[PDB]
Amino acid sequence: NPIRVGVIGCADIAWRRALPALEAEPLTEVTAIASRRWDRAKRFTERFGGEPVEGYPALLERDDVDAVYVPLPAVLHAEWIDRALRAGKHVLAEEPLTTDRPQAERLFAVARERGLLLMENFMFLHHPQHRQVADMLDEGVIGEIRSFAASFTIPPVGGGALLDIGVYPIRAAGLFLGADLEFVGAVLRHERDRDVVVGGNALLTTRQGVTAQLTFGMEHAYTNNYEFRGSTGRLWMNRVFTPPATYQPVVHIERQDHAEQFVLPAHDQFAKSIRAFAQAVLSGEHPREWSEDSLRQASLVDAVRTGARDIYFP
Ligand SMILES: NC(=O)c1ccc[n+]([C@@H]2O[C@H](COP(=O)([O-])OP(=O)(O)OC[C@H]3O[C@@H](n4cnc5c(N)ncnc54)[C@H](OP(=O)(O)O)[C@@H]3O)[C@@H](O)[C@H]2O)c1
Ligand SMILES: Cc1cn([C@H]2C[C@H](O)[C@@H](COP(=O)(O)OP(=O)(O)Oc3ccccc3)O2)c(=O)[nH]c1=O
Ligand SMILES: Cc1cn([C@H]2C[C@H](O)[C@@H](COP(=O)(O)OP(=O)(O)Oc3ccccc3)O2)c(=O)[nH]c1=O
Ligand SMILES: [Cl-]
Ligand code: NA
Image (cartoon, rainbow, N blue to C red):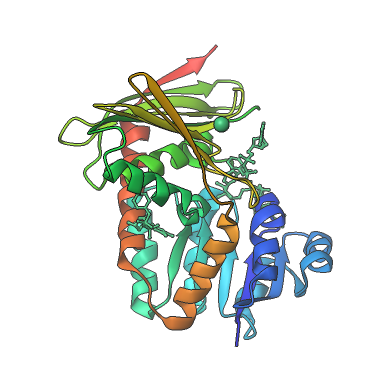
């Protein structure tokens, strides 16, 4: 008996990743899609099934809905996740969960009181390539880790590039370097014209001095990678955040006089993360690490927003 999923917001990202996945996943059934415009709802249900609903409250009211996918704009997550939890729906919220740490704690508290799952959807965490990369690092392939770089940049209620893009490299640092990451300094470029963060660069460190240099933005050519400098080599990889389901990662390693590349298996991370959500909802095993990782994440992001030097242009 698959969990019945309602989607609120007919997002691009739901159109391209989440709904195809929801659709293909046995453990989940798309029962309802809601849109500010009935026609858009409808364009979406013709594609992926379910009842097209106009407005989001109406979908929260349905009894044929156990869980809600929220691919809305970041600044609008808090209202709707909070409303979906209050209607008794478990929630799968696109990254970032929300805009700040204190709002993230409140959404988790609302969920905790009702025993509902609130999961922040970082598709990338669900791709086995990261763990294959981490096992190589643990095996010593480049000796001790000295520092980490990650970059996600792309060509040009809005999030801004910190919230919508910066979050990836920052989560990757969190994933690889651990829970003690502290802000050191960052810069954020803001476009005066539309008043919006369009890119930036952050520097973090663990307490042992393993630094992370994270780049993000939307005024750039596409890059989507990370790099580990160790005491005896380096390791980098491309398409680390959004590898296609059929794309085979290639781990690049260099050491003195020697370089290697390892091709890894293809994996559907969007499928796997929908499956992970469905599993946690069906079993009621809601891993604590997830919510504690989201809280820590939200803190580094607030740390970056606040502590960054902000620069307006021109
Ligand atoms: N493409 C991206 O920008 C991007 C990149 C990485 C991550 N994400 C994450 O995925 C989530 C959604 O982004 P997306 O890329 O799929 O963006 P999108 O196409 O803007 O989707 C936002 C959707 O939310 C609904 N919405 C409700 N109020 C809105 C408003 N005032 N203005 C615009 N849309 C409104 C709209 O759905 P209805 O019209 O059907 O109501 C719209 O289709 C965000 O959390 C984002 O951080 C997005
Ligand atoms: C391959 C590729 C993409 N894009 C553009 C196309 C698109 O605008 C953007 C991201 O493409 P993707 O990494 O595929 O990420 P998702 O669409 O899954 O979702 C996100 C959207 C925005 C932020 C992050 C994820 O870069 C390019 O400009 N060049 C490329 O080679
Ligand atoms: C799934 C997932 C994890 N985490 C947190 C929870 C956990 O703290 C961390 C990773 O979760 P896991 O993918 O199970 O761990 P592996 O060893 O397989 O992958 C590694 C890959 C690289 C380096 C370390 C581990 O992210 C989340 O916040 N959300 C999620 O959806
Ligand atoms: Cl490559
Ligand atoms: Na600041």
